[PDB]
Image (cartoon, rainbow, N blue to C red; front, side):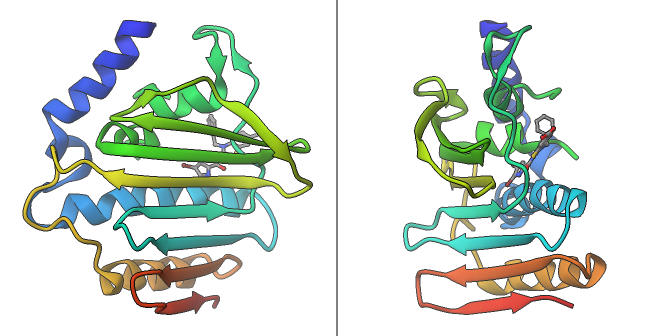
Length: 195
Ligand SMILES: O=C(O)c1ccc2c(c1)s/c(=N\C(=O)c1cc(Br)c(Br)[nH]1)n2Cc1ccccc1
């Protein structure tokens, strides 16, 4: 279990184009955002009047936040770690957010679910500690922030607002019930897509 997880993530770094697309022309880099957004849209669609927030941070990390159910935090018996950790680290649990985690120098997960805030940090897909309770909340949802690995992504390594805005406008149109916010903390640029 311990070694298959490290191997599944290793397999993604060994053949990254097969999982995320071109790692040199900016395709793969922006696909990283699209993969997390697709998970948030899928959650948004599972509910009513849900909202997704996509933030380009000033340090060229991206966060994707939904106000959905929250990824489950209970122990997954096969692995003996939180379901959230399994979803983030096990390739076989639509390539999945585990690809983004494998190709991220750092990833931060914050889940709001069943009265509690839960947080976990990853480096190159490796958890730094078990998912932990950091406090109380009556909000629900999932926030993923990721810093793409420059051991994978070459040449085009800076996120382009217009590439994210165009995809999110398409996704707003195709999912007319979902609110999508895009925020660029590098310059204060902000858009709200809601059909
Ligand atoms: O409450 C449940 O039964 C339940 C199940 C799956 C599940 C959720 C809730 S929320 C969720 N995913 C997201 O909300 C999500 C993923 C990412 Br990346 C973002 Br941003 N939001 N799921 C999907 C899922 C979670 C674990 C295992 C399998 C599917």
